[PDB]
Image 1 (cartoon, rainbow, N blue to C red):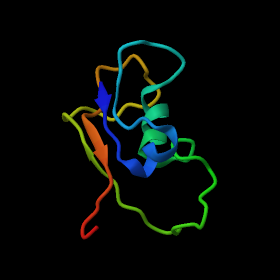
Image 2: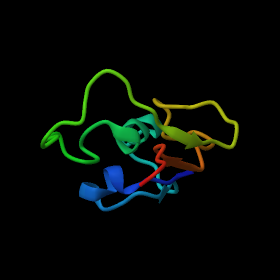
Image 3: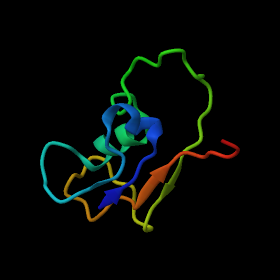
Length: 87
């Protein structure tokens, strides 16, 4: 029932790692896709553009089913960070 994020998306939102405690309209996947790299997490304005064809994103899950339309799920993941080597 928690997640983590890199500056890739936290650059605009300001929040990378979050935890699930309260229940509301926000679904489990609704925030997952956003936090993963939907757009609102880092604004729609790409500014310069990086590319559109393929993207890699590593995530850490406890081993549960990735739920989306079930905010009242029994957990989501542990952390989420995109690949990066070299600097």
